[PDB]
Amino acid sequence: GQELSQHERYVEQLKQALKTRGVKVKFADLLKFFDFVKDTCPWFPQEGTIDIKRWRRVGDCFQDYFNTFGPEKVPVTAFSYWNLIKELIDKKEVNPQVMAAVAQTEEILKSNSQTDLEHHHHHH
């Protein structure tokens, strides 16, 4: 999430995507959930493929994790945020603003790693 928020070319396309839905959120607020998919689905960037057929599994994952660890561990808003990206990818075919961002995210996923740098802190 905060990783993608630093890639300027992707940020330009996301400025269109955040705005076009009319949802009043900051980039920090959106990309917070992009961090959440990496932490819950470490295999998603390994597939390096961003299509709704792949993205549906991310929500299935949040649902499994939600039933196992409760709403205090996974928020119900994670599904709400997830739904926003779900419609964006499902209809990327008529949304070139996000389609370019889908391609850019795949490029960045393939260029990056599941883990890099001293992320020596998990839990709280």
Image (cartoon, grey):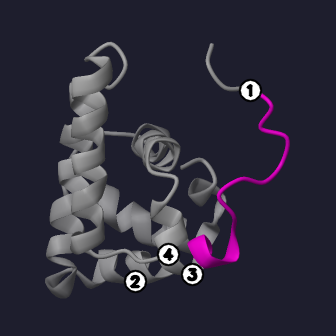
| Secondary structure mainly formed by the magenta segment | loop
What distance separates the C-alpha of mark 2 from that of mark 1?
33 Å
* Pick the front one: 10 or 70: 70
Q: Nearer the viewer, residue 124 or 24?
A: 124
The residue labelled by disc 1 is 121
Q: Mark 2 is on which residue type?
A: Ala
In the picture shown, does residue 37 fall above or below 16? above
Mark 3 lies on residue: 107
Stretch in magenta:
108-120
- Amino acid type shown at disc 3: Glu
Q: Residues within 10 Å of mark 1 (few under 14, many from 20)?
A: few
Q: Secondary structure at mark 3?
A: helix
Q: Nearer the viewer, mark 3 or mark 4?
A: 4
Q: Is residue 119 above or below residue 102?
A: above
Provide residue 81's location: percent of width, then percent of height. 26, 43
**Residue 48: which numbered mark, if any?**
4
Residue, disc 2: 100
Residue 74 picture location, percent across and down: 33, 25
